[PDB]
Length: 242
Ligand SMILES: O=C(O)c1ccc(OCc2c(-c3c(Cl)cccc3C(F)(F)F)noc2-c2ccc[nH]2)cc1
Image 1 (cartoon, rainbow, N blue to C red):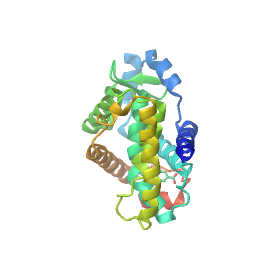
Image 2 (image 1 turned 90 degrees about the vertical axis):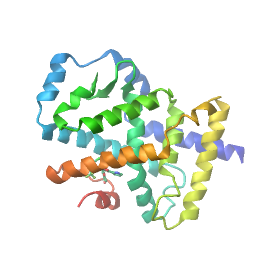
Image 3 (image 1 turned 120 degrees about the vertical axis):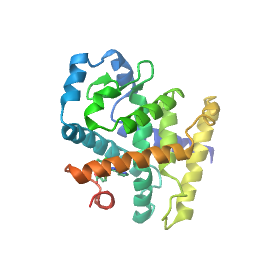
Image 4 (image 1 turned 135 degrees about the vertical axis):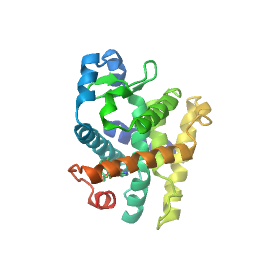
């Protein structure tokens, strides 16, 4: 069924298009729109907890778009609810991290944050310079691949649909989805003469370790200074918040 796989490609790309928050053309246009030194200093003088509140809410929104992305993946809703949650808890923040590279400019090492581009010194008040530097470096690595929009869509679908996640109840069912998405991805790379990115993608442990350091920091901030979340996915919220 060649058209089944082509239909999967089109359905993954559409779900991605509907949930990607900002258009790539917008991010690229805005690359010349850079925070002044005066604006940077304004961010640096903000309280750690106000920066935390801002960043925690951007990350919450980013997670919720990734959840909607997964819910629109063919067959995701047909998994048992325990499995949907296992997959989202393990991979939705990894997808957020991958998606960030779209908003990263490697020429000057800046990210699109709250309407303009700025460097990692924008986040000085958070006092997490090691984590921030790891996120920038990871985004720097990915930007070298010059990911197309469909590659990011297909790759991030696979970040989520991983039948090796511990705790899955219907592993065979997740495997079926995973095989079709892998075929979708590899077919698409072949059609576009882009199979060379396959050897350049992040080692799986790199993404896993960055996200576990990232989420652990968010849990520390959330314990010290909890933000209020507009919970759209009760079974998922319940696993992350306590
Ligand atoms: O709308 C909903 O129901 C909903 C449900 C779950 C949900 O989790 C968000 C989340 C967080 C996080 C964030 Cl982003 C901000 C502040 C504190 C945390 C904290 F660390 F405390 F959890 N970290 O990892 C995640 C995560 C989710 C899935 C994988 N990982 C956000 C929204």
